[PDB]
Image (cartoon, rainbow over all chains, first blue to last red; front, top):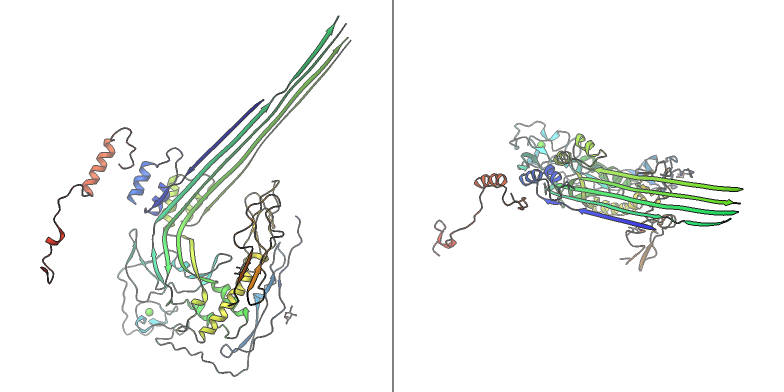
Length: 48
Length: 487
Length: 48
Ligand SMILES: *[C@@H]1O[C@H](CO)[C@@H](O)[C@H](O)[C@@H]1O
Ligand SMILES: *[C@@H]1O[C@H](CO)[C@@H](O)[C@H](O)[C@@H]1O
Ligand SMILES: [Ca+2]
């Protein structure tokens, strides 16, 4: 007799105030491969 | 499909009101008693009947235009607006015969985007803009320089603030569940003698697998905030002219048409946005059975052997995307089935700046527009309009509509109820699906109108509507019974 | 530069691009103070 089980959850929740409307939706688009933010998009948000 | 369609019914007519002293007409109306649904025949008749009159009661309809009468529209405009180089009357009347014109705006100045769209009142029950109530092309002098990015804008006189208020949210979830099982059970037995022998075998497998993947990603982008002034408002002339056509006598049908033409409430504060909701929902299953047996005897001899082997695999997957602000090239590529590459998302949000939807909004009942500086016998028109507004809410609220199959949602536009169908079910009632069952979300019947005065009660039931059939969701959003003072 | 996780120590490419940007908009890092009330000379009743 054999039994096996798995579970996974991910939640991620970027929130932004200030920024240009497009740069905001750029930065806040969550990267599974880089959950903090793509550095160029983040720098562009920090410009906008 | 399990249907026999419901054709429309309006009521038998009211008695006539007596003739109005100022409108010189009389009116009769019917309640909508049962909406058109399942493509049952409409009976709309534009919901009204009206006739002329010969009565001679006194009328005080001459509320003075103090400034200048806009000859076509019947608006009045204050005298500093004549020859301001702008159309304050609607039909350019104010700028006739200008011995000089004086300009004010030193530069070209865009309207803030959607500011003329916000100018229209909502039917709060379909959640729809119906038609134009405040003149968002009126500038009262104005020409104060406002900026968003490097673009420059003109603010309508009616609006307190339009400002970017530039805020954004993203919320993401991914979930997986998996479960596996495998069982194998066997038997073997033997005998021999010197002559005879015997043998027996069983082998077995039972197996199962399951997965879900669920993903939801929502973004809300809020890159303008609108607030309308509290009062001192300047009305759109098409609204103003149905208001000047309302009876001072009470007969609900003429007041009903104002809510149809101009909405139930006017939009007073709104956050103006784009939304990009994405959901991907997956359920996956697999199963197997394998079974194998033998029996043998020897003395002469005999053999029996059997195999039974089985497999199933399935996926059900649903995806929904909603996007509510931007420009059509971005909007379609976001609307594509794939999770949007952040360049798209950038160019979409950049266009939300130029074409928002309303995200969240606070609204005031339209009778607060009706005012003594704008209409004769105004306070009677208000009291009438308040009563009609309550009766209209009882008509437009969806509760009359028979329940959709497949957890469909009714919105009751015009005088027809049409069931909006989710992903995975189709047809007029949303019946047609490959699926076994769907969870149902609850809503009440129409509420009982009132009990007596000296403490008054309203009551609601869910008899067909209820969640328990096929294991539904929430039954409720408010109080299953309701009571108040009479005064 | 603020985005840099720092596990490497300073990434001179980012630190220099930031430092060039600091030339373009500084912040007060240390300061030498005199009391506000010594300043005023224009106003009527200045001394009072
Ligand atoms: C008003 O409505 C009833 C219901 O059809 C009709 O018999 C007739 O139009 C009445 O005046
Ligand atoms: C009947 O009465 C209330 C009015 O306060 C409605 O809002 C509701 O539909 C209830 O059932
Ligand atoms: Ca003018």
